[PDB]
Image: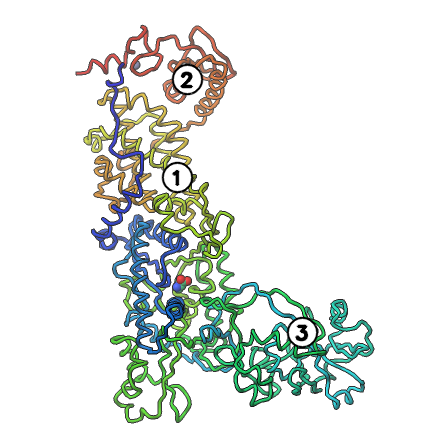
Amino acid sequence: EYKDTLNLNTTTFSMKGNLSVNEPKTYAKWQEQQAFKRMQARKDNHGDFTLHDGPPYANGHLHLGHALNKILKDIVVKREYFKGKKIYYTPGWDCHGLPIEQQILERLEKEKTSLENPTLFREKCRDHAKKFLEIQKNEFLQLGVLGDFEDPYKTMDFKFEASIYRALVEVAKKGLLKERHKPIYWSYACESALAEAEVEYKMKKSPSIFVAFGLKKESLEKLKVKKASLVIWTTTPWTLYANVAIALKKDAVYALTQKGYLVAKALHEKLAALGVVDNEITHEFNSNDLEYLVATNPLNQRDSLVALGEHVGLEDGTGAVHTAPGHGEEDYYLGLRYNLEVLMSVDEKGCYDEGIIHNQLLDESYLGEHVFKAQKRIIEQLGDSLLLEQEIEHSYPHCWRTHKPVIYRATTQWFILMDEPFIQNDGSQKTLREVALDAIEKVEFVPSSGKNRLKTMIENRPDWCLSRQRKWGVPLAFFIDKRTNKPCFESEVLEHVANLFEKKGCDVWWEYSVKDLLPPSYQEDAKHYEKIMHILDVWFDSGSTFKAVLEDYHGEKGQSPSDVILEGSDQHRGWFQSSLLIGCVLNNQAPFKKVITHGFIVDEKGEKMSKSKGNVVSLDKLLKTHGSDVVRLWVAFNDYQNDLRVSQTFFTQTEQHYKKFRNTLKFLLANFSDMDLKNLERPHNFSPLDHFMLETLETISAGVNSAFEEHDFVKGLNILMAFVTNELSGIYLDACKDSLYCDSKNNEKRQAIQMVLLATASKLCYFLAPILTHTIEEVLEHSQALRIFLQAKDVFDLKDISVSEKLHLKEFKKPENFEAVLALRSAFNEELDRLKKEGVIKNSLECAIEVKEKALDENLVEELLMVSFVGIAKEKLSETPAFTLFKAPFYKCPRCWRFKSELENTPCKRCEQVLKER
Ligand SMILES: CC(C)[C@H](N)C(=O)O
Ligand SMILES: [Zn+2]
């Protein structure tokens, strides 16, 4: 056998990734060697790119959605680095808020204990955030991501707390921070007000009742009827105690039935079909003539004013709306328009308090009962006034961290106003809603559809309630002047508190006296001031990160506005919106130039993962099973703008993609491993097939790059994979295998092939480096030729090379046109496939071909079809309009296995000379 006389063509680069063992070593080296700092220090940086990290909550281990997020950020950041830019990417953690505090409260409950000291309670929350920040940081690094993880930002840093407070101060000084009294979301489980981002709408079952309020005797006399009762529909019997009015649609017809029920005429047919009221209408009245009549509450016998409500709907209900100003925002405004009582006797824990006794609103037995528990007994107490009881299902607001349904309570809270004109930085006058809508139009959204998701929210959102009644967060640290009952926004007071926060953190707001928290020129008047003890919405904390990270560090951690932020599409309701709003107050523009969103990680069926459903796949399990480079390729090679399903089949497909990339890289490294590096300095004469491959490589490289610039990594990876599978493996490597293994190492044509393979390996490395960074690091570690060719110590020295310059190509060389010869190749292979079926031949090398069209390079035909002979032979096998196939009129060469030998078992002329070489 002559196998030992072939070129060895091997590389130390292994076919097996052994990713579970090798990736941790790579990532630990990048940490020890400070690779990100090295990236930022790269001397030839040209241009800047800032990605501003949206901070995860510092609670719990990372979930799969965190990995998706940081991997996508890493690909985007690494692309910009390898394009040559100085990168800014400081990851951060969201350390305050119910996401941390609720965990402490649940632990205290489970341990059967309490912690009432505010400093010690906050210390427990702060230690909890410190613990999981370190856990999450190290779990991020296990993904192979690069950023300033050894100097991340933290909302609990004292300087950061001061930054958040200084952001709040800017909002106050521009006149947008005001107190309001009105019903808002109230979570009784954590005894706190909430705003929209802290509410999760879920389906919930509820009573649904139709209740008769009888008109008082004097109102019946005014209306000239013997019996009349307005029927209301409500899903909240627990607010009936607080009824003050029944609101009707203005200028609308109301039908009185024979049994004496008064409902909107437009709803009578539906209501009679339900059995709420009887079918016979006796009289019709205009609601304008019913206004200021009075009815009687059947629950507590109190008066109820018949009023006219703006936008009373006739789609559902009865057209008569039970109005409780203490527990509904539109009810509140109507009560004020009619100067009615605001009845609100539900405490911070959602229980009826002594106000139901003092005001005669509800029987004393209900004192202390939770409003939701009391509803069944309230419904029974309604007696004959209850015309119909149903149970319905509806989407209902729940607290984001306690998961309990919220209620609504009239309360005094602090708000950022949306429709209050304020002075713009350029001197003009606009409302916050107007500025934010203008700002959104200047932001690039990827996908574009995200723009209108955020725009619709800004169009419809109410004033933003900022004040919370928990302890773990930044306080709304203003004083109330008792002489004025107004807050003190004097700059000397606010800057004094801000400076204290920067040096000592916000604990002092609880510990110091009012006098110790005031400037020395105010301390004799300290008796007139009281502290506001509410803390800020944690969404204000995170909406302020642009100011605390980008602006307060003066560009050292990135520019404001950032170039890119990248988060789940659920951040339209969260971080995108709060950052937009705060940036529009401070700067009158969004603090980001571009928003890229991704979907959720879901299970095999497309459902969200939760321990309740038992479908959770841990990040640790996924990484140990597949390796991080496979998980990273799974992300990049899929439609990450939508939900990504975790299933064995999809990860097996990704592993097959990774194997094809890795096997291709291994073949390349193996087949230029023996090349004399003196080749790199001299020009080469490339064949037409060589040139076709170089020109194809340039064409697909432009396509991969354009797709990756759009963040369409699927499109670019499909282009790359098709090139690797078809032109590279299917055509070029197949055609080149004979020369690579059987030609002399000194053969000039073989050396030119190796140069093409080096150029191809180089482009594969550049384009895969952002995604498969560990693997390309390993490629360079095993190929001295690649490192010298690219002038690269390691993966962080990669640049986009000019193949033309490195291979000394001539500028006006006319591109190859292989359309005719590739059409012949495809037709030959189909004919060859048929002959292999019949058993006529086993291989293309056994064949000779005579091509009808003599306008084709015959060496190229032989190369591309891998026949052993182009021309006429003696034993005809088949004929087409395009060619005739014969058995090759030679023996198989024992060394190269081509049918080119004149004598049996004797090396062909090429092999003979290679074997004799001195
Ligand atoms: C600010 C935002 C990213 C928030 N901490 C979250 O994890 O949803
Ligand atoms: Zn041979």
Closer to us: mark 3 or mark 2? 3
Q: Residue sitting at 22 percent across and 22 percent down?
A: 746
Q: Residue at x 44, y 22 (%)?
A: 825
Height in image: 598 above or below 592? above
User: What residue sits right under mark 3 in the picture?
Assistant: 233
Give residue 579's position: percent from left, percent from top. 41, 67
What numbered label is drawn on residue 733? none
Against 517, is 545 above or below?
A: above
Gap between marks 1 and 2, in whole Å? 32 Å
Q: At numbered mark 3, what does the secondary structure look like: helix, strand or loop? A: strand
Q: Residue furthest left?
A: 918
Q: Quadrant of the C terminus?
A: top left
Residue 41 placement, left or right of 412? left
- Neighbor class of circle 2 (other Cα within 10 Å; few <14, some 14-19, many 20+) is many
Q: Is residue 197 visible?
A: no
The quarter in which the N terminus is drawn is top left
Q: Quadrant of residue 11?
A: top left
Q: Amino acid at mark 1?
A: Glu
Rendered position, 456 above or below 520 = above
Q: Amino acid at mark 3?
A: Trp
Residue 200 horizontal/vertical position (percent): 50, 65
Q: Are marks 1 and 3 in contact (CB under 8 Å)?
A: no
* Residue bearing mark 2: 844
